[PDB]
Image (cartoon, coloured by chain):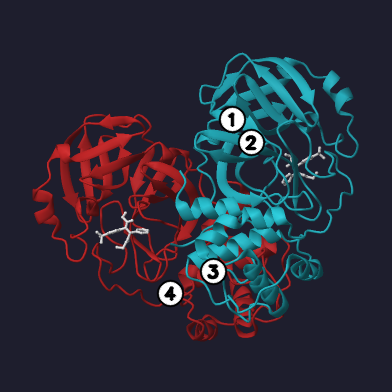
Chain colours: A cyan, B red
Amino acid sequence: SGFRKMAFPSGKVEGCMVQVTCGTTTLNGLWLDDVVYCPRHVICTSEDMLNPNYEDLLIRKSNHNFLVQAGNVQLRVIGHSMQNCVLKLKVDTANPKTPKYKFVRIQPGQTFSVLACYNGSPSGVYQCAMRPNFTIKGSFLNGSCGSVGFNIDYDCVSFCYMHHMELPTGVHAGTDLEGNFYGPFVDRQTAQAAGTDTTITVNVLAWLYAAVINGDRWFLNRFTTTLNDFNLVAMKYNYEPLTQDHVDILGPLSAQTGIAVLDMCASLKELLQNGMNGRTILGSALLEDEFTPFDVVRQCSGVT
Amino acid sequence: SGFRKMAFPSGKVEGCMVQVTCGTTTLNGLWLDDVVYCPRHVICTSEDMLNPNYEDLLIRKSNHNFLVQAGNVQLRVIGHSMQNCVLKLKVDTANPKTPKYKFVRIQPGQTFSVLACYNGSPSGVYQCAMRPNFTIKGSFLNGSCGSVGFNIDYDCVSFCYMHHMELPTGVHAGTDLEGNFYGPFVDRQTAQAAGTDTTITVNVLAWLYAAVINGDRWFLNRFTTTLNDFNLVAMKYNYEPLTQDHVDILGPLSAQTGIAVLDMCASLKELLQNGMNGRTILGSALLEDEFTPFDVVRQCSGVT
Ligand SMILES: *CCC(=O)N(c1ccc(C(C)(C)C)cc1)[C@@H](C(=O)NCC)c1cccnc1
Ligand SMILES: *CCC(=O)N(c1ccc(C(C)(C)C)cc1)[C@@H](C(=O)NCC)c1cccnc1
């Protein structure tokens, strides 16, 4: 029993982190096979922050200008190319610690672990969610760029995020491993306001099922609702609309607990309307939305 | 910017996890050098739960009765001994992935990361604190025993916890790596009620400093207090008493922010007396106590 914000074991990803330096800028890179992936803003200087022309800046760079260090040993760069907002540095050596991997572009509401790194070295691991406004609420300092987000299925690492920047509001923006930003963000120091950060309704419901499985049941009520009635409440509280696809994904949790999805929606509706009255659920005083239905099942079943 | 419940990178510990089986009981073991450490309750059957005599049960076991598997390869057991509540299985092979390590017995209020494992395989990593009542609020299912807690200082892993059991209240109890339980708990299925789970005051203050560093400042007030006045409030709210040692450890955070420790205590006193009025601090609606002053400094400086 017990329910924690759990991250995947980070070992497989730690073995891929390298330090990339170009000129006087240093950030993290991801070494998989004979390619090092890193944010293309590694080529930017202090004056190439406001409006950089990456193609023009990249013409002034050769293979020897990219210094790639894995631990204390230097990697030989034999090629470089730009794909969207990432640089791919071909090196002459395949990473011997390369795990089985995939590149995935996640949907908003999905969760993943981040291995925060600085100068190619891992500092910590934590669990995140891609917000509906395509930002992530991370913990990243200067030099953390190139740190990656990932999920693991037995022995396969699915990389989904690469950190690029911090918006002026303290939230984080980045790309998939093809260099395409999540959301409308650009790798430029400009006014980029984030949109409405709505609550991930299907995740809050999954967490309420996790609470029931663990003994926190005070919020269960004698009521039920409909998808349309619940969604009128969700819109009022800036919660994402709940669809039949969401109800379907909550099916195993509904079956395990014996609580119909719509009955759980009615408990959520009452919690939104009345608040928690100073009470807690799974050690939290607010409704947690960074656990997907898959995460709840995984943690509650012990998937290794 | 941003502040997260961050765990240490778990790679160094993942390379030490093994599966230990004795009879029909399987749990996790920790392979360091040529020794595998695991809870001695691996020798217990369904009838040796109420009042096991570990010395008598261990006489019926030989080296070949302990099956130790590291991944898919079997380790040869050449010795076995009981030290307090842990078994030490001498194997014929030193773990090639053994990191630099130490065994430390932590104090209550200190934090550490847990690598939850099942059948020798890691499932997830999360950050914990040793509660003042010597329990940990973890996430552990059946078979998680032998999973370990640790801290890392550059390249040295300091193991501090080994999971042994779940109390009937859903909280967790375990030992240091010398097999000595934290708290009064015994490795027996009996009535073991936990004591008052008080709040770790020095940690809440460290987290309030982390909030200021990150821009969450609404709780800062125009008041100050004294250690004795603050402690009268702390006793009323089941917070641990704050000592001058605690004030001293908060010195770097006080210096960085320019907010005197006693001024921050006065903000905490007001938050305890008035509550949060529906507001949040670092994305939390309650006062977080599982970040030590060292953790705040580490995360806010990017220690790898
Ligand atoms: C890795 C670099 C870094 O820390 N940045 C950062 C600086 C500059 C840029 C460009 C050249 C694209 C404008 C991108 C990233 C930080 C940042 O986003 N600063 C504002 C632009 C940063 C700070 C903290 C966390 N992540 C990133
Ligand atoms: C690893 C074994 C396990 O899951 N236990 C457990 C069973 C039995 C014992 C003895 C023989 C000492 C009574 C210890 C541990 C679970 C447990 O504590 N059950 C009640 C005794 C368990 C369950 C969940 C998380 N951790 C441990």
Considering depth in this image, is A270 or B268 the residue closer to the camera?
A270
Of labels 2 and 4, the one closer to you: 2
Residue B154 % position (x, y): 48, 41
Which residue carries the number 1 mark? A101
Query: Are discs 1 and 2 less than 8 Å apart at CB?
Result: yes
The correct choice, above or below, for A23 with respect to B218 in the image is above
Specify whether disc 4 shares its chain with disc 1: no
Q: Which mark is residue A283?
A: 3
Q: Closer to us: mark 4 or mark 1?
A: 1
User: In the rendering, at what x and y percent does residue B199 appear?
Assistant: 49, 73
Q: Are marks 4 and 3 in contact (CB under 8 Å)?
A: no
Indicate the amino acid at tag 4: Asp
Element type at mark 1: strand
Question: Residue shown at 44%/43% (left/top)?
Answer: B122
The residue tagged with tag 3: helix, strand or loop?
Answer: loop
For the residues beneath circles 2 and 3, the answer to whether they share a chain is: yes
Amino acid carrying label 2: it is Phe
Chain of the residue under the numbered disc 1 shown in the image: A
Q: Do labels 2 and 3 touch, CB within 8 Å?
A: no
Residue on which the image places disc 2 = A159
- Nearest to viewer (mark 3 / mark 1): 1
Callout 4 crowding tier (Cα within 10 Å): few <14, some 14–19, many ≥20? some
